[PDB]
Image: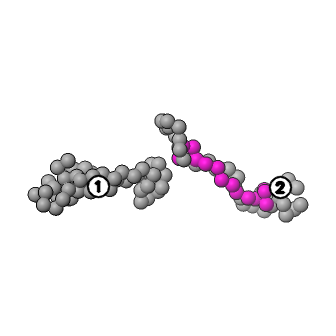
Amino acid sequence: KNNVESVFAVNGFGFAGRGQNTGIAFVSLKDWADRPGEENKVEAITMRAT
Amino acid sequence: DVITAIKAQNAQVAAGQLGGTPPVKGQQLNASIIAQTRLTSTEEFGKILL
């Protein structure tokens, strides 16, 4: 809730197969001035998550 | 009569998966059905109800 603005999660739809196995979720991130760095930068939001 | 055999004997028809399209509350298996296929041999063709 420090970086994330919102999460759109879609089930039956990925980019690979179209089955149930496959889904994805587009995450929107907080405004531009409301982030320092490195811990608010996409590269690490990602590291954390992955 | 020969014509209308090669047709039904050699067609190829659909039938759902299992889950896939709206399943029942809590499901553990989804996989595709495989109904009729098309013949693949001279001999395989030879064998047709006429």
The image shows residue A6 at horizontal and vertical percentages of 27, 52
Identify the mark at residue B48; answer none if there is no mark.
2
Range of residues picked out in magenta: B7-20
Extreme left residue here? A36
Real-space CA distance between mark 2 and mark 1, rounded to the nearest whole angstrom: 57 Å
- Residue A41 lies in quadrant: bottom left
- In the depicted view, which residue is nearer to us: A12 or B44? A12
The image shows residue A4 at horizontal and vertical percentages of 22, 52
The residue under label 2 is which amino acid type? Ile
Residue A39 can be seen in this image: yes
The local crowd at label 1, few if under 14, some if 14 to 19, many if 20 or more residues have their Cα within 10 Å, is few
Residue at label 1?
A27
Mark 2 on the same chain as mark 1: no
Q: Are marks 2 and 1 in contact (CB under 8 Å)?
A: no
Q: Is residue B43 left or right of residue A31?
A: right
Vertical placement of residue A16 versus B30, above or below:
below
The residue under label 1 is which amino acid type? Val
User: Which residue is at a point 78% across and 56% down the rendered structure image?
Assistant: B9
The local crowd at label 2, few if under 14, some if 14 to 19, many if 20 or more residues have their Cα within 10 Å, is few
Identify the mark at residue B38; answer none if there is no mark.
none
Vertical placement of residue B7 versus B32, above or below:
below
Q: Is residue A45 left or right of residue B9?
A: left
The image shows residue B32 at horizontal and vertical percentages of 58, 48
- In the depicted view, which residue is nearer to us: B11 or A33? A33
Q: Is residue A36 left or right of residue B41?
A: left
Q: Is residue B48 magenta?
A: no
Q: Chain of mark 2?
A: B
